Length: 65
Length: 313
Picture 1 (cartoon, rainbow over the protein chains, first blue to last red):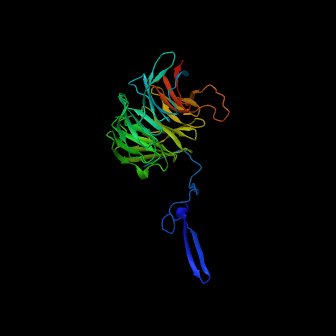
Picture 2: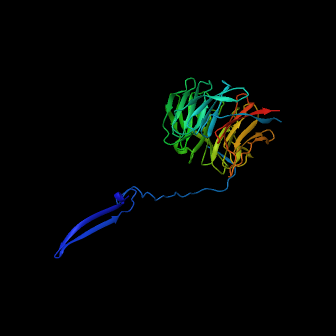
Picture 3: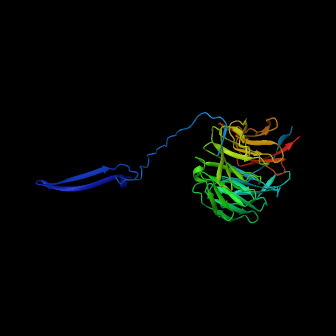
């Protein structure tokens, strides 16, 4: 996942006493479509769909078209 | 009243028996499907040592075989699979003459039309689908279909009302007109998902069942409800007798029969104990078939066997 969730750069700056190093790393948000970040999710992020709108009681009936 | 007795057993399988099929054309032959990917054709015998032998095996499907049915001439058989593909077999060579493709998941049941000129199928793909015997699809039900997996599809046996019936995991039973390609009627009542639907040979009644353990009767042409029978724990399969006013059900580890004149249980069929250190000690019954003679019953099980019962006085 490091090959598509992390963006990185390395740079040099020269001051009067010598060179300093800079390193920057950023971790991207998941974006299902929109190109802010990757469309592919993290490998261990399971998500469960919610159950909806059932009726508990029933009685036998028929309905013609 | 009449009472059943155990005749013998058939042993040539390596996974759960999924279905059995029979015809009046060849009373020494039966055909059965399994989770071992293959369909067996049996030579039955009246010898005292063993009731039958595996004669040929059909091997072309790539996952479990879910349903199997035979042509009214006894020359051909049709089958569906968990690989999503549907196949027609010549029983003389043991070879497929045609292959049906166009489901995109997993196929749960199939049937031939009563004239044997049309084929129908149901699947986890939520669509009922109609086919010509030349392997070409002709209609798709789409938006008006079940909201969940289509568990079963069947034809009415009579010619003067050309209709099909179906049950699904959305706990509804539905009736459809063939030539008009449309829904006729819903039936509502069951609390769990449905495993099966069946129709009487005179073309008059449905029966249906599943997780709720109740068998419910319904009219085909009057369009209305009839009485409910409490089965027990669960319903795996249902069938009517060919020459008695009886309904039969496979229910967990046991098989049961109701006489519909006066609505009473005739007998219940059970297995000798093998002591087991856990719940569900006995193996379950998965499928049923009455012989064309009506006097003998075949039943399939999760222990890789087919068990045979005769009627007696």
